[PDB]
Amino acid sequence: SHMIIIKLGGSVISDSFHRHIVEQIAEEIAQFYPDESFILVHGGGSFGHPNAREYKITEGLVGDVDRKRIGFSKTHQAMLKLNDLIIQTFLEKGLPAYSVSSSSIFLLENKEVVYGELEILRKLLELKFIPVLFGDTAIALDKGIDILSGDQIVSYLAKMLKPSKVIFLMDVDGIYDRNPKERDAKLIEELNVEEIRHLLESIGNKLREALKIAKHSEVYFINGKVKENLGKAIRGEKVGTRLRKLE
Amino acid sequence: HMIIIKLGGSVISDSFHRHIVEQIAEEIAQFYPDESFILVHGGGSFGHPNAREYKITEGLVGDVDRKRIGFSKTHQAMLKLNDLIIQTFLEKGLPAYSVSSSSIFLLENKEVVYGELEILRKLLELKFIPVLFGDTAIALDKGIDILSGDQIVSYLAKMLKPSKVIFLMDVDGIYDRNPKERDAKLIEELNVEEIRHLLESGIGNKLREALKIAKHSEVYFINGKVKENLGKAIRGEKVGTRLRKLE
Ligand SMILES: Nc1ncnc2c1ncn2[C@@H]1O[C@H](COP(=O)(O)OP(=O)(O)OP(=O)(O)O)[C@@H](O)[C@H]1O
Ligand SMILES: Nc1ncnc2c1ncn2[C@@H]1O[C@H](COP(=O)(O)OP(=O)(O)O)[C@@H](O)[C@H]1O
Ligand SMILES: C/C=C(\C)COP(=O)(O)O
Ligand SMILES: C/C=C(\C)COP(=O)(O)O
Image (cartoon, rainbow over all chains, first blue to last red):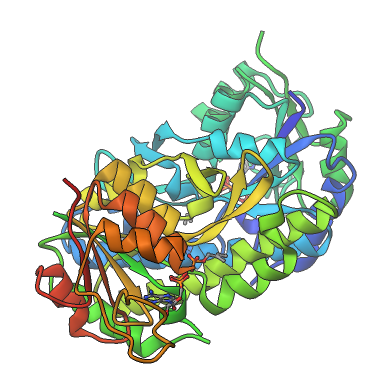
């Protein structure tokens, strides 16, 4: 199954669009298209988080339900705008990135995907297309509405489609000790389960979802600012933090 | 209890006629939330100039890479038009939500042979107004194709079985011949025999799809550029062309 999932962070695409960044990921992906299939998932940044926390989407369909539904739709549109920005950046570089609305195929419960539709994603990957999903608002079976993050989408896609690897693009070089902003913090080039539990005792949700994904595919945590990193993660070279498939 | 409203391409656009969209929004607001509504708006002056250029109807033939690029660009333009329509609906207080047609529907022979409607069902249950659009689509036979709103509403009528399906067109309804031709008379009560005659001698596609929708729901053909025409069509009053449910 020649397929790799790539999670674009929210801080590597915005804070304002980072066009040169997305150009770099597109240039790096063009090295393997179309022999290797690729799925991308991008989060919020100056688009999704403002409207998501302004209308209290995570609160659910409680209180003023009409305003909550209106803000639900508004946040969906605001995320579609940034998705269009990314799609145009990918199309200018010759990559046939196709937008797939996350809220149109996924249903939520306990901030997790309990219902999904993936035949369209398979048909896109088969026809040498590159699907682009996003952390979105979503319908939740428990609290009416919720915020479906990109990590949960990646987890569901890893459990179902079973990619060869999942590569997270973060602002730091990878999984560090304590906090990367500290003066002393060594990069974990080889991350395992016990280390993940150690850091979880004290990100956080990302490491939980990574522990879940490692059951199906390898996981990479690489710095998205460096262009050559992604390729090194696709070819399997030593870069950033690597969590091998569980045995 | 559910009403499927199809918005014609020559109605909403051809360029964007925002005033008539506000008019339609008020018309539906006169009934929300006593009834559930599914909107389907055509291509208009957004998806037509792209699909007619890139020849998406020809399929994945010739320059397949350029065809994929045009696929994605057409989807993005349709998303832009859908964003305009949904913002217009949101300003009127109605909670309209975007549903990408290419994310849940698969095509073969210009017809939906695979669909996903659970998210649509949950949206209708939570008092939302799902808005779909004539969109690019993955065709199982020719790779890529153009899924029109008529096929969308046909599949949705076969599946969800709404109470009635109202087509907003540039004309007052179905005429015994071309409305451009003089002495044109508007058919008040439409039946299968007149449809057979009009087909045996665009509009023909809409008649073909209405013949299939009539087995599940009552069809209306009214002028979209006239406000009250919608309400009279929802209240079952005499307006435009009326196609009773088959028996
Ligand atoms: N041990 C650690 N390893 C890695 N990052 C750490 C660690 N401790 C703290 N951090 C901080 O966690 C932050 C990671 O941000 P976060 O997990 O919220 O994701 P993001 O960039 O917002 O996007 P996304 O969730 O879409 O990937 C960084 O700013 C980093 O400094
Ligand atoms: N017998 C007829 N009755 C009414 N309109 C007709 C007839 N024959 C042709 N037309 C015209 O043909 C056009 C077909 O447009 P159509 O494909 O329905 O647009 P859309 O795809 O946006 O719904 C209509 O604008 C209509 O004016
Ligand atoms: C609108 C969705 C948001 C802000 C969450 O997505 P994430 O950044 O967790 O991928
Ligand atoms: C790009 C979508 C198209 C061309 C379909 O438009 P409709 O027939 O629904 O008006």
